[PDB]
């Protein structure tokens, strides 16, 4: 019996901010560039009562709702916008889920590839026989950790995705993976800094030495291991900080648009970091058919890349029978203006010590 | 910040307070009596019906209906940590097991669906930060439709 | 058991207004020495004090008894403290009644105070007297409870389309009573029209909140003639307690009182019903016997208490108010000083605020006098009726 | 007036130790239901509760009465709260005595608790129950007051060179009493030598501080036989109050008690002297009649209270202790459970901690029994004797 | 020859923010309260290239333009929102004015009464014979030092006023003054804090123990010294943090509306702190007649009050002949939205270290 | 700092508290009775000796002697705002008018002069900062020799 994904879930903020609302204030980038070339018209706004833990536990609880009475054996939280810098937020999510304390547990960090790295850890724990199952979460509040006036502000979002790994009722078999990494400081966040920073100007030069190099290296590595090529895959899923990014990487690695399209979700969300490759995968599995082949290649700034190959099983049809797809979830939204978004995300420079709510 | 002179504060919470209530606040656990099966929220040590000490944790129903609802819009009554969202929709939620929970409704995407008798479900959200610096998490409700 | 008489009662005037120039000690002394003078009594005749406040979180002064005994200048005479929301004074009155009735003390000063302005923003502190881990720390206030209670009352007793009319008629009657009452915050204010009130905050049913201290002096019957010609007797009291948690109003198996209504909630206060029934049994009266009353007014809470107290039937208090039932010529005159809306509210003092107007009524000294008043009743609550007090006074 | 009997008394064991796994509600329930069982009584027979704690600043729970009535499962029965430093339970006992003696309630549960670990650092919170603007906010603690009181006692009554000997002998006797008392925090610990104690913290006279709840059940005399064969009667009580401000100990014209000593201060507690004299007059006893006692021990405070209480003359308590006077075979056995040093201290529970050991003594059930004990006395204080309570119990 | 005011000038930011723009975001106060009771419909917004020095030197240069070739003998800068906490901004303004270095010079601070305190210092320097003339400036950027979400945000403004004191061509003779002070911490700003903080909740209770007590004490003090009463004055000028404040204080001290009205300017400006009493005075002198009597009573939180009595001279008619009044100056305005106001006033929580303008 | 989310705090002091006590705390003003001339510290409204309300402010003597003294060295009992100076020398000071003040002795330049009966004088010092951010000032004592 093969090992892989059994169930999944997602958590996305409902508040939305149209790109023009940010551009009207800062006038620091072209509206047409962001809407048409990059492919993002609005982005998710984090409410004051939302964070990585609230989104993560929502996604996780939605995955576990598919498997009544599941006892948790391992739980790994992939995030680069962790609410805690010491102590594991994973243990907080575990406590909330209320399905066992005897679990392998940690937070995992490598930027946008944190979620795929957690997934690989969970696969290794099941495949080794160290556990019978394992829960991987990928979640980020990129909005919260992107500065007002930053060139990326208008498309910084947030999100969470949860994948349960096991060997009973598997809907996507985990076939193989390949990872790579290096010191490439294309983006950083030094200890203390709230805001994620760029290491150079934005554009294809920065993309060539990080995003494209590592994505290519991992994809070619895995395909070489499996003796496959782009033609052998029904779907390809990349990092989706922007709608343009998967299409661009696909053109760079010899995949074609119809292999990419079914993973695209982020036009109304923006960059969800660690969640983005996992959300692309979820968007595929929501409509995929038994027998189909998926290649998933994430990207973490810093930098590195995780490549994973999957095969969809017969069980996907039963899983799909009564399932709320991600496409439907993303229809739920509340529009807010720029001022309200900044209030909600705690980006006004207010007093260090508050006397009342407003003094 | 620049002058680290300690400021006076009568009260600082120990982690023990919230530690013991994770069942109640993360998982909506009240109590059920082992002898007579009566249910209560929040959690307790003595059954109120029969005065037995044989009481166990009980997972309350996480789905319900809005029994009664009231906007909170008055700036004068804005609590610290809750000033940013205005209005807040305060509600008494009747759970499917019969218990009633005092909470609020959030993420209202269609205002015409916010009415008495509307179905709701529990969600975990961030509440006012603790006086020991730990983030506070607990329940709120959303419309379920 | 022996009878206990009130020989004087007094409070610092305009309790819906603040006294920022005074300390809490100065404010306590004002009302205490006023009452002592009214009774022709020396401070050193006081054998004990029972005094109430919200708690130590306002002024950061705890263990307050000795501090009060020193401020009043009665040491070594003890001060027993009471910390019980808006019922603190009502509770301290009951404590003093027990002190005298026991025979342990013959002359006892009962009272309470609140100095909200010592706290930067008292409004957000008050929630600390609730089921804190499941309401206060989630940003849920007492005012939310009253808003919800009012909404439940109107939605379930068929008042849709007349909510504004009911609340405005109530608030207008309070303003009418306050206009000619010198100790009231709204003393001398012109009476706004019903329409102006409907279009104002809370349809005119928002209370006036300030600072005050107050007290009543209790004496054993056999001594009362030394201090007054016209003593007011305590017939009976009840104090009752249920969970602070608002959810429990709808389902509280912990509350053991037989013959409650089948359907209880916020609009039907089970704790308040139980309290009234116990009190009346102790006092040897029924609701029929009540000539004048006091209730904690705020939004529709006056209606809920009118029903709990037994003055009118379930769901009928709104119509009772609309038909003129609480006016001075009505079937049951209520809050004849103006109440919390007209006279004013200061949490820990509220019990004495009620008792003083009833005291005056029962001696024929009220500014809005109920002719031939024999029985007067204070219905007071704390939290959302987590505390409830019913105090029955007579004049013979 | 009618007599009031204690039918049971109990507290959560090892009160000098903490119970971090319990909530305050769970802890209260433990001792309450233990006492109910000891008395062969059902919770729903309780007609009222009088309960004490330090204040709302520890757990951020105020208006606690209803919360306790719900926790115990007695609603609608009321809980009257008491907030009075380390005398909270002593005061609540006196309140319950009044409740029963009045005839208003026949069966009353008296008690108190303290959950210090709910606060991050309780030690710096306690100062909030003082004359706060002139001590707490200047960084002056109750412990400073006791250190100073001890220094004054020794410097002015000629104990120079024997301070360590006095404090160590006291602390050693407390440890001896605690060793064989199962409910004590120092139960079963080996007795350190006098020399080891002298070279340790506070020469062995530092208290053990933890968490506890406790209660006693009071019943009208005519009902006591239903619940116990051996009732313990309340002979008389006094509670007295002076300023919290430590300076006033030396000069307090506000304290009107005739025949006080000429020279008063910290080493000579005027408030405590007054309290004892009042209590004994009410109880119909003198110090001669006392067979066994309890005092708030900490540093030299036990000595000051031994003198205030009338057990030995001014300045003689140190020598009384050195000569073996508080040992079980001594002239006046004192703190036979181990006291705050041996048994342990939890502020709001301390009054019941005293009363329980006296209750046991007066029924012949103590682990360090005083043969033929007829009269037992609790001397307790709050702040630096700003509150003072003296409670006199007998067995016939 | 009597001593007093010879010439004056004002400096006001041109950017404006309608009150409803702030209230729409924070919903923390009533629109009707601020517009109708308090009397403020819009407020001044500080541009990124404006501050106390920029406004101060504008006002001062406008006063000195009335007296060609004036050599400066003293210069005092009254402000509670000083660009420097050590070193005197007054010496920077002196340098800019380019009219002499040999001057008595310092910064003066007592909250909203800083400007009137500087004025008293200048009067004392001339009346003592220590100088022949002296330049007083009152200026504040209250907006810059009021926090986002503060109850006072919607009516925090900025401004500067300059008054030249001398004994040649005097237009308003300085008759007498009376000052008072005490420890009343009704508002504070501790060393370091950017934002000015309240010591208690807003309303008539706070007003009674600071604003009204000190204003009354100084006004009654001065009138007792001169054997005068409110009926003896053609104009009264108070602190003008709000249009409502002068009318309220007038009602409290037995002045009537017609005595106050000609000093009112702040309906479109908001609170200009140290500048506000001096701007009220300027607004009076722009239209006053020879012989008329003015009472000026300022208010500094902390707290204290400066009262000054003046008499208008024959020279006012010549001064008025070719003069741009303050009323006209305040017609120059540029409307901005909330987001833009927050950008301009540096109230977004951006990164402590900037890599470019937008990264 | 970087995340301006309001933290929970039960109690925040109004400026009114200290405003009314500036006489007591800056100037060592207690009270004197106009009828019987008895003196008290701290200030009060009713004379304790005779119960008259005719009471006026009284400037206490600012010189005195150490009546009793005790070091505070126990870290367990260090209050916030007072942790930096160790030991603290707590004292009851007997003023030249007979009143006694609870305070501490600071600036002890010669330790051999710190003893019972030593003459002291009042000084104004910074105490623990207020919960509304204002600096707190009040009395302490120094040896006067
Ligand atoms: Zn049961
Ligand atoms: Zn006197």
Image (cartoon, coloured by chain):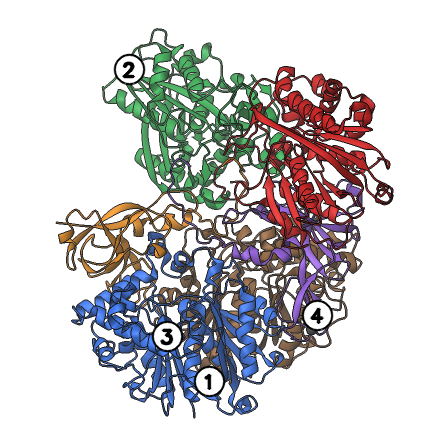
Chain colours: A red, B purple, C brown, D blue, E green, F orange
Real-space CA distance between mark 3 and mark 2, rounded to the nearest whole angstrom: 79 Å
What chain letter is assigned to the residue under label 1? C
Residue position marked by numbered label 3 in the rendering:
D339
Q: What crowding class fits label 1: few (fewer than 14 Cα within 10 Å), some (14-19), or many (20 or more)? A: few
Q: Quadrant of the N terminus of chain B?
A: top left
Q: Is residue E12 left or right of residue A97?
A: left
Determine the chain carrying the residue at label 3.
Answer: D
- Residue C392: % across, % down: 59, 75
- Contact (CB < 8 A) between labels 3 and 2? no
Compared with D389, F65 (above or below) is: above
Q: CA distance from mark 1 to mark 3?
A: 44 Å
Residue with the mark numbered 4:
C311
Query: Depth check: C130 or C23 in front?
Result: C130
| Residue receiving disc 1 | C222
The part of the image, by quadrant, that contains residue C258 is bottom right
Judging by the rendered image, the residue that carries numbered circle 2 is: E73
In front: D90, or C301?
Answer: D90
Q: Chain of mark 2?
A: E
Question: How far apart are the alpha carbons under marks 1 and 2?
Answer: 86 Å
- Looking at the image, residue B131 lies above or below residue A240: below
């Amino acid at each position: 019996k093969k090992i892989g994904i059994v169930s999944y879930g997602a958590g996305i903020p409902v508040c939305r901010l149209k790109v023009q609302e940010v551009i009207n204030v800062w006038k620091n980038t072209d509206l047409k560039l962001v809407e048409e070339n990059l492919g993002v018209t609005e982005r998710a706004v984090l409410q004051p009562d939302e964070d990585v833990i609230t989104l993560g536990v929502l996604a996780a609880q939605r995955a576990l709702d598919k498997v009544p009475g599941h006892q948790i054996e391992a739980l790994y939280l992939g995030t680069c916008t962790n609410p805690y810098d010491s102590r594991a937020s994973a243990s907080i999510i575990l406590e909330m889920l209320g399905s066992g304390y005897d679990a392998y547990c940690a937070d995992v960090q490598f930027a946008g590839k944190s979620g795929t790295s957690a997934l690989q850890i969970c696969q290794a724990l099941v495949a080794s026989g160290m556990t019978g199952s394992a829960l991987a979460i990928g979640a980020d509040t990129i909005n919260r950790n992107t500065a007002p006036g930053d060139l990326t502000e208008s498309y910084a979002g947030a999100g969470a995705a949860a994948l349960l790994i096991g060997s009973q009722d598997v809907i996507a078999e985990f076939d193989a993976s390949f990872s790579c990494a290096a010191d490439v400081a294309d983006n950083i966040r030094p200890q203390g800094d709230r805001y994620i920073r760029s290491g150079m100007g934005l554009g294809s030069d920065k993309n060539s030495i990080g995003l494209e190099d590592q994505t290519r290296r991992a994809a070619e590595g895995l395909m070489a291991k499996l003796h496959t090529s782009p033609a052998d895959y029904d779907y390809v899923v990349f990092q989706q900080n922007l709608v343009s990014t998967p299409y661009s990487l696909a053109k760079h690695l010899g995949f074609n648009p119809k292999q990419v399209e079914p993973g695209i979700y982020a036009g109304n969300v923006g960059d969800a970091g660690s969640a983005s490759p996992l959300l692309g995968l979820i968007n595929v599995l929501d409509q995929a058919r038994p027998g189909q082949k998926i290649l998933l290649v994430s990207y973490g700034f810093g930098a590195g890349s995780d490549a994973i190959a999957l095969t969809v099983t017969d069980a996907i049809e039963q899983y799909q029978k009564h399932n709320k797809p991600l496409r439907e979830l993303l229809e739920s939204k509340i529009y807010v203006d720029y001022g309200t978004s900044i209030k909600y995300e705690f980006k006004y420079l207010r007093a260090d010590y508050a006397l009342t709510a407003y003094l | 910040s620049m002058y680290p002179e300690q400021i006076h504060r009568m009260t600082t919470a120990s982690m023990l307070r919230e530690w013991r209530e994770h069942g109640g606040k993360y998982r909506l656990e009240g109590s059920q009596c082992e002898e007579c099966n009566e249910i209560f929220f929040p959690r307790r040590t003595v059954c109120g019906a029969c005065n037995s000490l044989s009481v166990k944790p009980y997972r309350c129903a996480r789905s319900g209906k809005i029994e009664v609802m009231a906007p909170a819009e008055n700036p004068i009554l804005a609590a610290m940590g809750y000033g940013e969202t205005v209005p807040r929709i305060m509600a008494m939620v009747r759970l499917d097991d019969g218990l009633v929970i005092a909470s609020e409704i959030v993420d209202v995407c269609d205002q015409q669906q916010l009415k008495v008798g509307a179905p709701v479900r529990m969600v975990i959200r961030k509440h006012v930060r603790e006086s020991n610096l730990a983030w506070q998490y607990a329940y709120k409700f959303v419309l379920d439709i | 058991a022996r009878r206990v008489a009130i020989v004087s009662a007094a409070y610092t005037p305009k309790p819906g207004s603040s006294r920022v120039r005074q300390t809490f000690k100065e404010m306590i002394v004002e009302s205490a020495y006023k009452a002592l003078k009214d009774a022709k009594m020396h401070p050193r005749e006081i054998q004990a004090v029972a005094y109430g406040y919200h708690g130590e979180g306002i002024s950061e002064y705890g263990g307050l008894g000795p501090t009060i005994s020193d401020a009043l200048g009665i040491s070594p005479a003890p001060t027993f403290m009471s910390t019980a929301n808006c019922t603190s004074s009502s509770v301290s009155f009951q404590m003093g009644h027990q002190m005298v009735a026991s025979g342990e003390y013959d002359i006892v000063l009962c009272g309470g105070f609140e100095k909200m302005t010592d706290h930067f923003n008292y409004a957000e502190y008050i929630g600390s007297s609730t089921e804190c881990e499941y309401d206060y720390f989630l940003g849920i206030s007492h005012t939310d409870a009253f808003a919800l209670a009012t909404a439940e009352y109107f939605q379930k007793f068929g008042y849709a389309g007349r909510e504004a009319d009911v609340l405005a008629t109530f608030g207008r009657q309070m303003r009418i009573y306050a206009q000619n009452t010198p100790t009231a915050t709204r003393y001398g204010q012109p009476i706004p029209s019903l329409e102006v009130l409907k279009n104002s905050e809370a349809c005119g049913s928002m209370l006036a909140w300030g600072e005050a201290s107050g007290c009543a002096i209790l004496v054993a019957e056999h001594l009362a003639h030394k201090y007054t010609d016209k003593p007011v007797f305590v017939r009976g009291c009840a104090y009752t307690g249920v969970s602070h948690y608002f959810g429990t109003r709808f389902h509280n198996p912990t509350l053991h009182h037989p013959g409650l209504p089948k359907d209880v909630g916020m609009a039907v206060s089970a704790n308040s019903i139980a309290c009234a029934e116990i009190a009346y049994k102790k006092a040897g009266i029924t609701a029929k016997d009540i000539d004048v009353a006091q209730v904690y007014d705020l939004l529709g809470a006056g209606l809920i208490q009118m029903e709990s107290m037994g003055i009118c039937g379930k769901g009928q208090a709104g119509d009772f108010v609309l038909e003129g039932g609480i006016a001075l010529d009505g079937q049951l005159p209520l809050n004849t000083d103006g109440g919390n809306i007209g006279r004013g509210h200061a949490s820990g003092c509220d019990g004495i605020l009620h008792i003083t107007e009833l005291f005056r009524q029962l001696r024929g000294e009220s500014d809005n006098q109920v002719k031939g008043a024999r029985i007067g009743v204070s219905q007071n609550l704390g939290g959302y009726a987590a505390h409830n007090s019913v105090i029955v006074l007579s004049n013979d």
